Length: 128
Length: 128
Length: 129
Ligand SMILES: O=c1ccn([C@H]2C[C@H](O)[C@@H](COP(=O)(O)O)O2)c(=O)[nH]1
Ligand SMILES: O=c1ccn([C@H]2C[C@H](O)[C@@H](COP(=O)(O)O)O2)c(=O)[nH]1
Ligand SMILES: O=c1ccn([C@H]2C[C@H](O)[C@@H](COP(=O)(O)O)O2)c(=O)[nH]1
Ligand code: NA
Ligand code: NA
Ligand code: NA
Image (cartoon, each protein chain N blue to C red):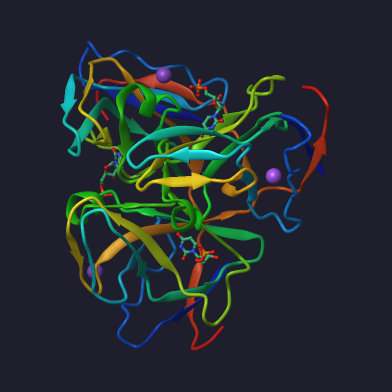
């Protein structure tokens, strides 16, 4: 299976091949400064068409907090197969626990794909 | 595959069907006000019997922080198949980074199911 | 059926027990750790593991971690790859404290499961989607 990837512009660093099954590091599309106790969407400079029936999960890298002092406000970001449009660029939602600077090209988070949950039948009951 | 769902009461909004594999939005069962730097378990007004051998994963929605100023203290909630009792209602563990008000019926987080990890044995060794 | 090889820091580490029905598995603080409000500490878990080939592990807080200890996990979910299998590749829990707190040696502070790694994928650059 394959992922089609469109970059925001030619200066974005092309990301790792995916022949191995490791999570894949994504990078700041531009410089982003965030003050202590403030929030910014860090653009990742990439848009993707994921395989039919899959979704992507995005979390911080292990070293992100140590080096940048940010947490990811939504814990883990879900990118559905449907977020496949020409302007559907990815972002990393960052809350700074201290004044910080992220520079263009800095690796800031990581992703993998996973099969979406199967079709399920929700049936209401009065008791369990 | 089916999930049996019990709602806290008649006023809880019945949630989305699960035909497409998308994550499913869960909603506040009552008004909850949270002060900056305080914590509250936000009731979701649902109890579920998940399919055998499955667990649920719960994370904020992408827009939760922007709209509500809360993060999920456990990052991703994991609800086991065994949490299927008639009083086993679900909660979103919220920490407010600013004063906030959540209203009854607001979408606050999302879940999916996933198969539990395969059978595995833990074997102590004296060296790797 | 599959196997996880687990090695402990020392004999004082309380050995981990697997939940027979496939539940996530709790891990324990390897030593006492004091963390001041708004400070960070990489809490040692006192375990190194060789995971099954083609698998990874996922680490999240327990539901009770915040109530008990007032900490959040700064990386959201830890990813432990199959390759992190060396004799000195000990696991940690990266804790940010939202209040002054003390964690005691042996406290169950986080939980893990394994999951198959994503399959091989071909990344293909395109000009438009
Ligand atoms: O951490 C995230 C979470 C989401 N998205 C993308 C995928 C979503 O489809 C879109 C937001 O749409 P809603 O989920 O808010 O509809 O943003 C990200 O780039 N990063
Ligand atoms: O984000 C979560 C995580 C867990 N639970 C369920 C399953 C737990 O067994 C139960 C109670 O958790 P503790 O009181 O053991 O933390 O809540 C949730 O509703 N939300
Ligand atoms: O919450 C975590 C996340 C990672 N690790 C381990 C596995 C990683 O291989 C290593 C850090 O390596 P990088 O991911 O920074 O390469 O730490 C942990 O013990 N706990
Ligand atoms: Na990369
Ligand atoms: Na609605
Ligand atoms: Na102990």
